[PDB]
DNA sequence: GGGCGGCCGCCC
DNA sequence: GGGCGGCCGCCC
């Protein structure tokens, strides 16, 4: 079971496990916020690439938490949705 | 803003609008449950086609209510998810 | 077959 | 450059 309200979230992407730090995601998509067991750090899109989902081009859908895409956590109030980078 | 708890729901797909009848949707995906203003009836997938989204092959995402896919209303307990065939 | 994950064109 | 709607192959 996963506590969606906790400041740290266990996440997965393509069978790769990591720990998402909400305090870091809140600083923006360019900030490394996911740490794998070996201590390495990833931004969300870097973690999408790590899990083999580079071609999907959507970390909010490629990265999952408790069997839900991160977008579902954002829609349900468990996870801040970081701002877009303007064009 | 849409009352997602109403038995009749205004839905859209592409430029097309219609009213989704929840009690008809409950019965299954082959049942006609969306009526347009001329009185014609559509299943969800027929309404997907009518709105120009034939190639999406996912009426739960192509058909919208209040800006949300119907899938969202199902995930949040406002709409029956008809049984899979 | 019905529909969903993988993909990527395209806008902003 | 980022990410979402449109597309479609392919499980069950």
Image: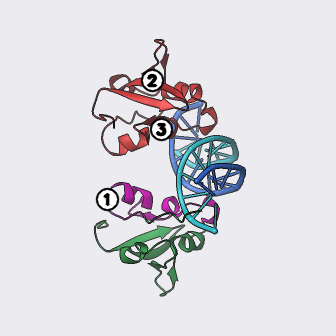
Chain colours: A green, B red, C blue, D cyan
* Quarter containing the C terminus of chain A: bottom right
**Mark 3 element type:** helix
Q: Give the crowd class for mark 1: few <14, some 14-19, many >=20 residues within 10 Å.
A: few
Query: Same chain, marks 1 and 3?
Result: no
Q: Quarter-wise, where is residue A10 in the image?
A: bottom left
- Asked if labels 1 and 2 touch by Cβ distance under 8 angstroms, the answer is no
**Closer to us: A25 or A56:** A25
Is the residue marked by circle 2 packed among few (<14), some (14-19), or many (20+) residues within 10 Å? many
- A87 sits left or right of A68 in the view: right
Tell me the distance, in whole angstroms, between the alpha carbons under discs 2 and 1.
30 Å
- x 58%, y 37%: residue: B57
Q: Position of residue A2 (x, y in %)?
A: 32, 67
Residue B23 screen position, x and y as percent = 33, 24
Between label 2 and label 3, give the one nearer the viewer. 2
Q: Which mark is residue B60?
A: 3
Residue under pointer 1: A77
- Mark nearer the N terminus (2 vs 3): 2
* First to last magenta residue range: A53-81
**What subunit carries mark 1?**
A
Residue B49 in view = yes
Residue B18 is tagged as 2
Q: Is residue A67 magenta?
A: yes
């Amino acid at each position: 079971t996963v506590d969606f309200k906790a400041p740290l979230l266990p996440v997965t992407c393509g069978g790769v496990k990591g720990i998402l730090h909400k305090k870091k995601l809140q600083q923006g998509i360019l900030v490394k916020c996911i740490q794998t067991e070996d201590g390495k750090w990833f931004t969300p899109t870097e973690f999408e690439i790590k899990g083999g989902h580079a071609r999907s081009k959507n970390w909010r859908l490629s990265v999952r938490c408790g069997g839900w895409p991160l977008r579902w956590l954002m829609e349900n109030g468990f996870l801040p949705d970081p701002p877009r980078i303007r064009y």
